Image 1 (spheres, helix red, strand yellow):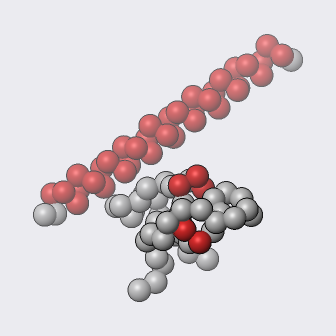
Image 2 (cartoon, chains in turn yellow, purple; image 1 turned 135 degrees about the vertical axis):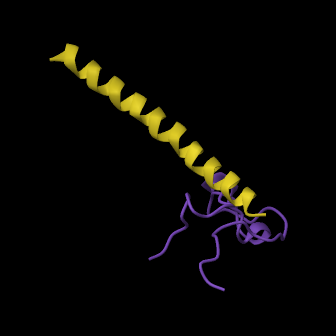
Length: 38
Length: 50
């Protein structure tokens, strides 16, 4: 079953980038929220 | 224990072991060898108290 593990290890590598590019948005949204506070 | 919150804390910077310099000029860098560096205010860890 070598042809089916590539579909899963490529999904783990792109959820890696998805939870990382969402992680910089969740840190830039609390920057410009507390920028409105001043 | 309590750790830092990488989301809610505004001034958080993920400083890895290569750049954490507590006991800077009195402790060998990344090794049990002889000391190296200068005396300098630390950057790790973040204060949980005070």
